[PDB]
């Protein structure tokens, strides 16, 4: 029993973190096979100009107590690729995967190439994440693990004025309309991930929280009319199919659960809690629930 | 910026998890040097009798794809110690430390010797933890990491009727008045960890949440009179010294912050949130705050 924000074990990613120093800038890098990936901001603006003025000996790469020799450098969008002469012997099976808003992943916060903490995050609908990063965390990566394969999905770059964070996939393509330089850019308006809230309500039922249930049901369209008023994402039919397995385990139809959520939005919780929370949590996917509530 | 429930990177602990099978029972074990630690329940009651009827070949220990040969067995309180012929080459620097109620630690949830997730926990004042464990998680360990040294503080054993969890330290001594057999035992009444709530309020101020602050101050004794009414632990003078460093960074006296907490307890939050939470969080220690809000 129990339900907690659970991150993937980080061992496979810890063995890939390195320190990249160029000039007076030091950040974190990701060492896979004979390539080190890090934010191109380390060379700091026309980055093509700045990179052409660099040489291999300008990049100091340290894997713990062993310095790696850079034999090549290249840029892929906002990510720098430093070729080294040594393939990382701890390289796990991995993939570069771009995730969707509403999906979750684990973050290994790192400083000077040294992991310090691990936690779960969701990609918000506005393509920011509500992370925990201090100065020197650039290059920390987000990831999921499927069996033995690490799917890298995020590299951290910057903090926005509202305190949320922005980054790229491992191909260097930013999530959202953000750029790796100082502008007036700010996060857009955010919405609540409706499908995740419903999954979380199912997790609550699996764990014995039932006070919010009711005998009512609603139509898909009548729920979305109420969800738009409370800044919730519209629920699609495809979201109902994904919530199908959770509906069968609990014997509660999705549209049955939607009626409870509509009641929770219109009335609040009245001093009660759900899974130890006094608000509606939207950072657990249906997969996260099944993984932890199976 | 940002504040999240952050666990320690689990790599150093993942390399110690093994699978222990005796009879038809299979659970998780902890392999350090040439010793495997696991709950004595694996031999299942007079455990001294059950253990005397066992032999080394009765214990199947598997470290991934390599079976470990048991050359000795011994019991230490509720923990079994299986001596193997191979010292774990991934053994980190480690210590066995018993923690105090109110302290936090990271849990590496494991199934069949394979890590599946990592999350933060606090030892509740009633010596239970609000974990996330499914069937087959016995032997999962809780730990802190200081620099390079892993302080193991918890081994999971059982779930109580209320859904909370109970276990021992790595010497096999239970936290709380619980025993490793089926009785009518239940968790006692719990209290809120007052010093941790105050630390969390400091983290909120460091992260820009200030709406709950006020110009009032209170005495230590007048705060405890209000804390006893809301099932909060009494605040001691020693708790004020520990909150000292957080008070200096924010320029807010501890007893100044106590007046805000008293107001929050008497009035609630009135629809507002603190660090993304609608209730008062008590599972962040002062050390956890300084570590993440430095
Ligand atoms: O991508 C960026 C980045 O990596 C860093 C950064 C700089 C350092 O000196 C570090 O030590 C560090 O960890 C990160 O700053 C930035 C500042 C911006 O305004 C915009 C950015 O895009 C980055
Ligand atoms: O300490 C205990 C324990 O380890 C297990 C357990 C049994 C299994 O068969 C497993 O596969 C497993 O992971 C754990 O059950 C218990 C059941 C009790 O009533 C009391 C206990 O103290 C334990």
Image (tube, coloured by chain):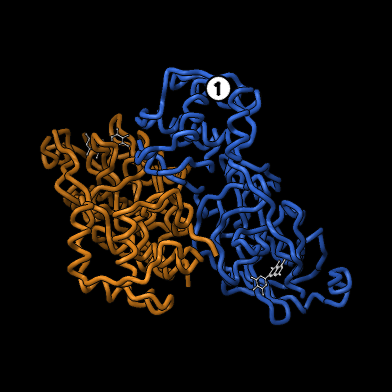
Chain colours: A orange, B blue
Instruction: Give how far across and how far down residue B250 sits, in percent.
Output: 43, 22
Along the viewing direction, whichever of A223 and A169 lies nearer the viewer: A223
B131 vs B7: above or below? below
Ligand 2's quadrant is bottom right
Locate residue B202 relative to residue A45 in the image: left or right: right
Along the viewing direction, whichever of B293 and A90 lies nearer the viewer: B293
Along the viewing direction, whichever of B34 and A97 lies nearer the viewer: A97
Secondary structure at numbered mark 1:
helix
B292 vs B246: above or below? below
Name the residue: 69% across, 52% down.
B188
Locate residue B254 relative to residue A258 in the image: left or right: right
Instruction: Give how far across and how far down residue B286 sits, in percent.
Output: 54, 33
Q: Is residue A23 visible?
A: yes
Instruction: Give how far across and how far down residue B186 sits, in percent.
Output: 70, 59
A121 vs B24: above or below? above
Assign the N terminus of chain B to one quadrant of the image: top left
Cβ of disc 1 within 8 Å of ligand 1? no
The residue beneath circle 1 is B244
Pointer 1 chain: B
Name the residue: 25% across, 36% down.
A162
Q: Quadrant of residue B85?
A: bottom right
Name the residue: 75% across, 58% down.
B178
B76 vs A255: above or below? above
Along the viewing direction, whichever of A223 and A207 lies nearer the viewer: A223
Instruction: Give how far across and how far down residue B144 sits, in percent.
Output: 59, 46
Assign the C terminus of chain B to one quadrant of the image: top left
Q: Residues within 10 Å of mark 1 (few under 14, many from 20)?
A: some
């Amino acid at each position: 029993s129990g339900f907690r924000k659970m991150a993937f074990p980080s061992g496979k990613v810890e063995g890939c973190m390195v320190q990249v120093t160029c000039g007076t800038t030091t950040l974190n890098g990701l060492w896979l096979d004979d390539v080190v990936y890090c934010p191109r901001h380390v060379i700091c603006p026309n980055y093509e100009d700045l990179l052409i003025r660099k040489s291999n000996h300008n990049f100091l790469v340290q894997a713990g107590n062993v310095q790696l020799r850079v034999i090549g450098h290249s840029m892929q969008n906002c990510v720098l690729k430093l070729k080294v002469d040594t393939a990382n012997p701890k390289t796990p099976k991995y993939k570069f995967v771009r995730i969707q808003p509403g999906q979750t992943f684990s973050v290994l916060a790192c400083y000077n190439g040294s992991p310090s903490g691990v936690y779960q995050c969701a990609m918000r609908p506005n393509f920011t994440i509500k992370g925990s990063f201090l100065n020197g965390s650039c290059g920390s990566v987000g990831f999921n693990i499927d069996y033995d394969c690490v799917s890298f999905c995020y590299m951290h770059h910057m903090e926005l004025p509202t305190g949320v964070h922005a980054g790229t996939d491992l191909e260097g393509n930013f999530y959202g309309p953000f750029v790796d330089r100082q502008t007036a850019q700010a996060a857009g308006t955010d919405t609540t991930i409706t499908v995740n809230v419903l999954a979380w309500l199912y997790a609550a039922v699996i764990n014995g929280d039932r006070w919010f249930l009711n005998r009512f049901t609603t139509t898909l369209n009548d729920f979305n009319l109420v969800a738009m008023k409370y800044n919730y994402e519209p629920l699609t039919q495809d979201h109902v199919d994904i919530l199908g397995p959770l509906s069968a385990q609990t014997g509660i139809a999705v549209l049955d659960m939607c009626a409870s959520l509509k009641e929770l939005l219109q009335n609040g919780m009245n001093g009660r809690t759900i899974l130890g929370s006094a608000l509606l949590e939207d950072e657990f996917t249906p997969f996260d629930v099944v993984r932890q509530c199976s």
